[PDB]
Amino acid sequence: NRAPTSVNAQEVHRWLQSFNWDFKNNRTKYATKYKMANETKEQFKLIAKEYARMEAVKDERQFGSLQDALTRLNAGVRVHPKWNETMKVVSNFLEVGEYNAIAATGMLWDSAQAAEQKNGYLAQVLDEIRHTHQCAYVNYYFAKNGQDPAGHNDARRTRTIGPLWKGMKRVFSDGFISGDAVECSLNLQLVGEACFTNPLIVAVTEWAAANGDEITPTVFLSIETDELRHMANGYQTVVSIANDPASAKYLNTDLNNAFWTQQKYFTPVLGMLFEYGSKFKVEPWVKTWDRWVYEDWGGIWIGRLGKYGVESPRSLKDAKQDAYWAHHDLYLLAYALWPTGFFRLALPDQEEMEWFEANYPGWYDHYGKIYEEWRARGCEDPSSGFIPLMWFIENNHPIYIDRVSQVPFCPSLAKGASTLRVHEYNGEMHTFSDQWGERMWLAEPERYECQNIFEQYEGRELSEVIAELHGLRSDGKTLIAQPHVRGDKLWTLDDIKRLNCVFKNPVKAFN
Amino acid sequence: NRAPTSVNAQEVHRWLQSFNWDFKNNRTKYATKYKMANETKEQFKLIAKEYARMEAVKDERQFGSLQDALTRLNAGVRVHPKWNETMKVVSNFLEVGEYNAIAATGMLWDSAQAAEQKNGYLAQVLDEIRHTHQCAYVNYYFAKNGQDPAGHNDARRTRTIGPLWKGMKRVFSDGFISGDAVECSLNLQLVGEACFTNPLIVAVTEWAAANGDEITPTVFLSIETDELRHMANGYQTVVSIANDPASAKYLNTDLNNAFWTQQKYFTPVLGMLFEYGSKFKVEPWVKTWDRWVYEDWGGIWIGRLGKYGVESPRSLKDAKQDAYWAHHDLYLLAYALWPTGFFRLALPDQEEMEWFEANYPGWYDHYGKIYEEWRARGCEDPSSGFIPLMWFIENNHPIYIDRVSQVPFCPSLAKGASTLRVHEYNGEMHTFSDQWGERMWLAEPERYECQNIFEQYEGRELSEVIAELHGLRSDGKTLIAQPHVRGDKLWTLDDIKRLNCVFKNPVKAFN
Amino acid sequence: SMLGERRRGLTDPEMAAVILKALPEAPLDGNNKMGYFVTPRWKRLTEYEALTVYAQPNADWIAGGLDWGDWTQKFHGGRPSWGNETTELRTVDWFKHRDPLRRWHAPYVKDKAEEWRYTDRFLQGYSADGQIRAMNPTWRDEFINRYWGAFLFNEYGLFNAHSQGAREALSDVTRVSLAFWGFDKIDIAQMIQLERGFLAKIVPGFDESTAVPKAEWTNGEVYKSARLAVEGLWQEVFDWNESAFSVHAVYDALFGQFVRREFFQRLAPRFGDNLTPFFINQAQTYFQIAKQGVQDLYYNCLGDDPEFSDYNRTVMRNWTGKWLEPTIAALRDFMGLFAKLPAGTTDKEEITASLYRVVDDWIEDYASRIDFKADRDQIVKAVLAGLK
Amino acid sequence: SMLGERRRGLTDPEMAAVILKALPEAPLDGNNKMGYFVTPRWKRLTEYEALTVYAQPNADWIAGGLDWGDWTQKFHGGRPSWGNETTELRTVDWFKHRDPLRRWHAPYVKDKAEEWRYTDRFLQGYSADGQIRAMNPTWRDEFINRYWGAFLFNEYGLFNAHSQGAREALSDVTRVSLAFWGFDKIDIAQMIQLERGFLAKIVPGFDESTAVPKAEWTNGEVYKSARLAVEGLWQEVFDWNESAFSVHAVYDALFGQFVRREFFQRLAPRFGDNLTPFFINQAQTYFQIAKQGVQDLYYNCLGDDPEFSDYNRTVMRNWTGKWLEPTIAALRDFMGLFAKLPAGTTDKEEITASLYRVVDDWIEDYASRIDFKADRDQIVKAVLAGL
Amino acid sequence: KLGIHSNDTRDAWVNKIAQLNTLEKAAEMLKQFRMDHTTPFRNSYELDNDYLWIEAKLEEKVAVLKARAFNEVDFRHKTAFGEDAKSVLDGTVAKMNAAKDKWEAEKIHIGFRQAYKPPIMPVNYFLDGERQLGTRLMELRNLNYYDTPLEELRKQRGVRVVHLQSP
Ligand SMILES: [Ca+2]
Ligand SMILES: [Ca+2]
Ligand SMILES: [Ca+2]
Ligand SMILES: [Fe+2]
Ligand SMILES: [Fe+2]
Ligand SMILES: [Fe+2]
Ligand SMILES: [Fe+2]
């Protein structure tokens, strides 16, 4: 018998579970309260070689479209200015999420004892590396072929100037790798990807296409195809510890803490990037958020984990109350601090203001009037000597940074949440924006010592910080960041220096 | 020393010329007046493995663009109707040229005695298989994702119904493989590709892009990347035979015949597909032709070969004289016989007639008026009971088929050439449209015995022919071919049957 | 400029608007399957079939053709562009053949390219790993450089035997399969040289020139009859099917398989040579791929033709006998090489058993398919006479 | 519908017009090179560097970082997400490393995918060609199944040793190389099982179960010192650099290379086995690829660090010494395998020459890089005593 | 029944061919058919639209009959008429090389095809003939190809000029 014969992935994976053997020190090297069953199985029966093949095939299509048809169509250029800027943040911020996920799944791979569960996490380790490079490619492509390379070309260092980056690291960097492996698994997979990341990636391709961007859909839709393996990983994480008695005592709290951590940042940030970083709208963020968080995640997803003792996050009701105006409240701060970014922002045009009011009754009387006031005052013109941060100072509206989530908040102006808790402990002041974050710090002060921008930049003149952190374009004079998206009247380092803006730690006013 | 080392294609190719060895019967199996030099060399130092890699890279980008971005953009649909129809003919007709080129180069590979020259032809054999499959893919893609699949989905059998197909087989099928290997090389490489095919492929991507088609550019631009090798093969053929006494005696004669053969079909057909098969125009055919045939080919390219005894074709002047109105004279015939095609045609619209009249003074007084009358006769309406062919009969304008080139012509109604030569020979009548083709037949009667559509369809009712050869849409009643490109009022087999059009062989009128 | 000067109908607002306006509300035909009229070999029509079948414009007078009428231009004398007269074999339809591996151009160059890049990685790993150190010097300098090298000309000759077929094949599916069978042969000849070139780089003094291997092929004794058979198959056969059939279902199936598998593949390892087997693995993979196509065309389609089955088998039986003798002669002369080996390398029993493996495989995969009455011990005994 | 309901800004006339109207006349910065601020290792910046370097958000307090401030969230206790405290090695810049092969995800899976599909093709041809007919039955059912298979647990173990490194690596370029080194190891282990699975299909009485090979690994005697050395490199080492260094520049470079290249890749051919070598060719290709990266990190970067050259070489010489013993021990326990080979398979003269090949390659490729003075004769002598 | 691919004429010849159950009779009919219906020298153009297809059907029968009647050596080296193929090939090439002009040459080549096309002569010999005969025919025909005026070429070919038209 000489019939052509071979062997596939499933046939090898069949005996993968037996690859691991017993010996005294065969245990995780990371602190954890849980015990992952040493017989846990994985959903996809893959071996290294088949994994590569299925991913290589996707790369083919993706890079083929990018290098050929899309380039021939000048797809990198024919994108709305506002969206070109938005993608600088979306792609780079997600990049770090993808990157730390490599470390996270590495930690999870070390945590799992069953060979198959380790193999499941391993596949994501590789996927996360692919995603890091994909998000990197989007910025690389828009830098090479876009209308404004600045920011796209150096976000890895220019992002350190702004406050939005700090919070991104909390949810997509540190939140993914610092803590109980299982807690990280919850931030990354059970909450992060299942509730936000996945729905977000697809949504982004929708807003991208609406604004002329066919580059992002080509890359992000490819990333999306890898998500079923990660959902399984997250789901299997729970199944792996469901039996352990410690689970009943700890799972729900790590989850709740994980849910709050992630929503605290994405609730305001995502809505902002979608509604304010685009010209053409796809759907109101309030509607989107409700579907994602309450219907899809909080309901169907969390529901299926019920048999494993998983319960709806106790802070869910709170998240919904704080959500409504969250993104609108944050854009005011983001724009007021525009010189600290690595992207260009625009104020809502007339059609947009109408869209905002139609979808968020009351929007115009608060946010709309403020933007028109700032614009008439010349916030878009470099010879005006006006930056919106000045307006906040003039009207005594201090801006704080939550010590835990790193999210900026202005309780005196906010149409949304306006709670503020300030504490002093061993010679250091702390500001919190909600009761959940306050507890985290109170219970785990050593986990949260992140210095905020006001602390680091205290006493420093704005232009010096920008210059030092390389917030300049090629000519070494024009700022990367801008308060408008037009091609003329770009602000320069000198236009900022003349403002004589000096940072102050707002918390010291309580002394 | 264990330094990472390997071997590339050139390093192996260095010894390829020595692969062939001597023995009594090592000679071509094909009849030829020429002797290809035993030590002829090739331009590109390739080996099978490297050839495969460079082509595989191209396929990757091509299919990636087609399957991903282009499909997501609905590129198969957003193309002007006229162009969707034009590509049915362009892609499938070129397909056969690509296909016969496989056999043609297999024949040259057999002809060549030097291993390197055989290898050069070999690479084209493989390229032509690629091009066959590529052209097939264009039709395949438009059938799968376009506005009108009929024709795109079965051209390989529906093209046999019409007269334009016969001429295509002469220049791109039989002309490529039947005759002296060198003669075939002239039709294929020295004339066909150099003068028409290469320039045509590029031009098609421009017209395609202008009409919304990004599918064809993706494939055809990839086809074009392989042409340098093919040009080298053509040039090398001349070099390999230049030092042979037979060359001075026969080369220019086979070249002149080849030139006339190719020009006779493409001069009128290309201009027709370009100008009449499109909405948006790129450039008038008159100027395109002069640049292609007279300047680029019959000047620059042809000159470079003067050192090998190659001279400008003696029939070049006649070609130009007959060229001017050629494509215009032909569209009148293709439209009049629209029920015999596998594509939908349209009358020039008001805006188009202006362009035609502007670029071809006198066009309106001749063709314009004729189309307006056919329009009035209801040539576009199924209930009119009218087909332009009837008009030719009523006005005694017989349409003949050149016995040699298969190109249809109406000498009584043509602004271009109006010569007609009719001979009787051993019980058969033959009709020629020019002095070059007439000479070909008189000297080589047994090479040209192709029966024409009138001879084959004589006494046959039109609807019966269309039905027998599967010229219908999937509903089994609506014709594939149409006299207009609109979505309603499509002609049915019954509409044709009612016309009771019965073919007659025009030459039988002669005594 | 950033935007460019050329306007595209897909993205230019004005032009796209014009295009969208002329579009129908829905496709003018729901049958969006190119090649729908082709009779599928398998469950559903394959991309391989759609893109290939009927590309060849044959008229009905060439079995299976869908066109009508004579060719537009023929050879001086009247010879048709393609015609029944170019082969003794007859069939109900020349388009019935299907490559079991369904290889059209794209999948074909993709796999070869994978093999090329991996080959390069392998060689870089082999050289860096210094594995050449344990290869027997005599095997390397004598048997690889001279005898394996001379075999490149055998494969080169079989490659060339396909030139006429590339021109005469009576259908697209057969032309594509034939082209690929031939292209794989030149690839192997080039991989033999590739190995010699590699050895010249990592082994001081090794000469990559083909002079020695070529002199062995053209004037040596070991390959004399092999070369005579190759010269015949290539240049004395004017029938494209006799050529493909005799090369793949007779000569290469017996002589080729014996040399590659029962001599070099079998003995190289005994001399610490894992380098040559790397390339023979490719040759054998190619051999087995081509076999499936060869079997489908000659046995499934022609040998089992509903109308010409008996006739075609008679002819292939004729060809088998015609070429079996020259093939036995080739194997017979090749037996002389065993005497050149260092004592104790192998013996008469191993050699005989290896001959039987090739003969038995041939009878099962080819001879039996056309009822050719092959006598295995008679063939083996005839070959053994060449053992010095 | 034929056109669909969704309107796209690139093709929709109305939306596209609005977009084109907002576009600037020319790019707002001529510098269209992402990663332009990265120091090129070669002539011009490569795609590999642009897409990888600085992806890790390290602050300046982690040698090379470009960010500032503490991490946002840390471990209970205060342990940083990534910190200098996770490895004894120090450097002026953790982003200096560069994979000689410049592998980011795409090229990496492209190459492994080519190997996978060619592997499949090879197997289909090998079986159809009946090449199994000439393989020594004992070598198959005993040395390939039991001893080669058992070695899959060695590679698998080395694979897992990279788990902590995947989590603790202090830079992107190093994390990617590490992840690829480990993934290749699991690949090899899965390839060993793949072969056993293939043999199971073409050889009627062959059992693919890992039971026999596992028992050999866990309770056997041939790989005893080997397994002990693996369990230690994997679960007793908490310094990600000590794990990678010791695994690749010590253990696998001595034991692993000997077993794969000097035992199976050298003896399999003598039993009519070109199958196993087909997979070892992959394992060796992978080994030589990883080696270039291992060398660039610990020698070109750390070992030759402009500020910690002496320091790092000391730590590595210490590690080399620390693990050279368990490795030599592993080689000794392995020597016992030759006694189970059929008489006349090989002699002491050959094995001695093979060991020196391994030891000499090791010295030239690793030991001499950090000024580690190893004695070839004493090592071979120490190992050879296991016969 | 007057179709392109299926008609009474073709049906009529299929029945006729079905009654050719002897090699000698079948082979003689095929050769007769070729003299009567192929090449520009055919005795008649009555079967112009179907002769190509009918010829193939005739060839099929002759081939099948020849394979049954001839031993292996003859199938390879004899024509269906029992002639030695090599002798016929050589004899025809000799005549071709003695041809005094392109007119004599075309008759030799064309006549060879009508009489020996493959089912009759083994393909190997027939295509070797195409190679040699074709070469000489072209050499003679392509020498000073344009020297003879059309007016005179028409006379040499012997056509009856029916109608001439020109601007
Ligand atoms: Ca008459
Ligand atoms: Ca013996
Ligand atoms: Ca017997
Ligand atoms: Fe991801
Ligand atoms: Fe994910
Ligand atoms: Fe081509
Ligand atoms: Fe070409």
Image (spheres, coloured by chain):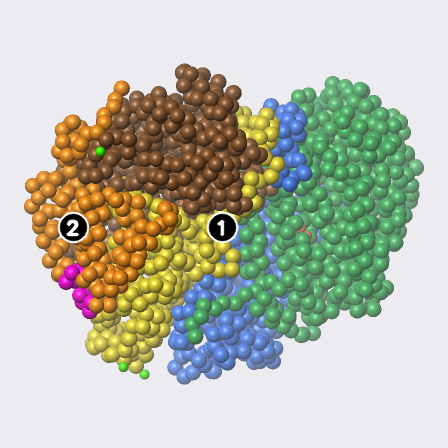
Chain colours: A green, B brown, C yellow, D blue, E orange
Residue B183 in the image: above or below residue C195: above
List x then y, in percent, for residue A50: 56, 60
Residue in the picture at 66% in, 47% down: D56
Residue A103 in the image: above or below residue A427: below
Residue in the picture at 71% in, 32% down: A280
Asked if residue E21 lies in the magenta stretch, the reply is no
For mark 2, give the secondary structure: helix
Residue in the picture at 62% in, 64% down: A45
Closer to the camera in the image, E158 or B197: E158
| Residue A203 in sight in this render | yes
Type of amino acid under label 1? Tyr
Q: Mark 1 lies on which chain?
A: C
Residue assigned mark 2: E112
Q: Relative to A256, is D386 on the left or the right? A: left
Residue A118 in the image: above or below residue A490: below
Residue in the picture at 76% in, 50% down: A195
List x then y, in percent, for residue A487: 65, 24
Residue assigned mark 1: C36
Closer to the camera in the image, C11 or A25: C11
For mark 1, give the secondary structure: loop
Q: Which chain carries label 2?
A: E
Asked if residue E78 lies in the magenta stretch, the reply is yes
User: Callout 1: 10 Å neighbours few (<14), some, many (20+)?
Assistant: some
Type of amino acid under label 2? Phe
Closer to the camera in the image, E93 or D198: E93
- Ligand 6 within 8 Å of the CB at mark 1: no
Image quadrant for the C terminus of chain A?
A: top right
What range is drawn magenta here? E70-82
List x then y, in percent, for residue E133: 15, 47
